[PDB]
Length: 125
Length: 357
Ligand SMILES: Nc1ncnc2c1ncn2[C@@H]1O[C@H](COP(=O)(O)OP(=O)(O)OP(=O)(O)O)[C@@H](O)[C@H]1O
Ligand SMILES: [Ca+2]
Ligand SMILES: [Ca+2]
Ligand SMILES: [Ca+2]
Image 1 (cartoon, each protein chain N blue to C red):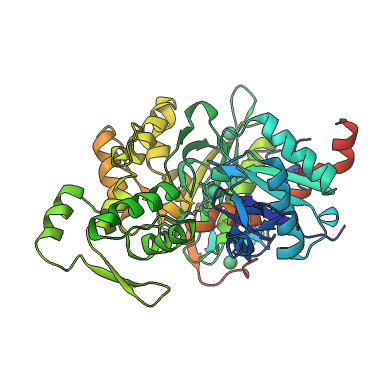
Image 2 (image 1 turned 180 degrees about the vertical axis):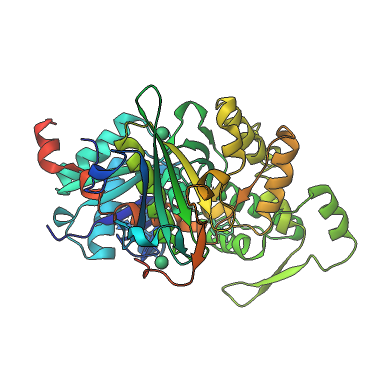
């Protein structure tokens, strides 16, 4: 029984960029107006879907860890990344991103730049 | 529908147990069952140790593998009732297992949970995988060293690579026993089971891993500063010198113990080499320590040197020593069993019974 989450049903259906925040052991969409501004107290999962010439979709999954995110948040971000990859039949390539040391590919998803801000959602622990 | 999972991490030396969502196990007790030497039928954990005079003590888990099922069931009963005060038949349960645990073993544990304890749902997790998740990673190699066994476990995009897992029969109890042995140099004759517990605590309090063993032997001989003291239960003081770093040196030089085995640095390297060349950089860059025997001061620094020496010079060696790593298996289980998706991961009792079974 492949593991499903309601957000998994929305994931990777069209080319684009989707960002979720870990909140209390769940995967919650980030409001699109706030894309690119990451709370240093939180952990996030990011799916970039690209349309390939052959017609198929390419998937890159990144989990981003803020410098003050709690251990439940970073652990859940890692696990939800695995589960979303599995839901995509294993086809996604997974990437760990740490605040201030992100890959150039990840940074490049944000036109107006990758930024950080203070705060974050309360720890589940 | 509203129900919190129990998380049980089964070790050779200690059981760690508690409730999903807690940041640490609230129940930690020795994995020991005592039964009358000659006429309960059985006693568990801390209480068994207080009745050693009239009980024969046994360890139901040997090198991470459950090997005495009747006594293991006593441990699980103690866990649910005495420690947690939980009805196992009313909670999902996450149980952990050793890397490379045979499927037949996993099945017996499953049969006991569903048919002895009537658990409504259960999930079995590999210990090293839970530790990696607790560190916020999906790819890396976990070095998990406990009381009875050490494993090196390469994990890629969430899953262990079975062909690359190493088992090493060398862990904390061997180190405790080695310290008991070398303390004879200074006139101590620790040998009883009770004395072993005392020496275990000495080891934990005073030992450390040298950055370079030969250089540490040299420097420690030049003065008495190496010497550090420990207050015994009877109020006497013991002083320990170079035994402080010679004891855990056996992790790197198992010949100290009369073992032919490779040390933990060599084993980690060999485990990485079993994986295809294209993923090794992510393993070398994410060597994650787990378990009580990884708690020695100096371990990260020493492993970094020694693995760097063995590995290709193009690799980027990073040894990660999380401060909570002692119970990172249990913590990873607490996180996993708290997720909104956990209910889709488990096996239900009805499914098991109709499989069947
Ligand atoms: N601070 C410390 N320094 C050194 N060793 C320690 C420390 N704390 C605990 N240990 C050792 O760790 C061991 C217990 O670790 P752990 O609970 O991870 O093992 P386990 O799960 O019972 O065993 P295994 O994983 O081998 O089946 C004991 O040998 C103990 O003495
Ligand atoms: Ca947070
Ligand atoms: Ca994949
Ligand atoms: Ca263990």
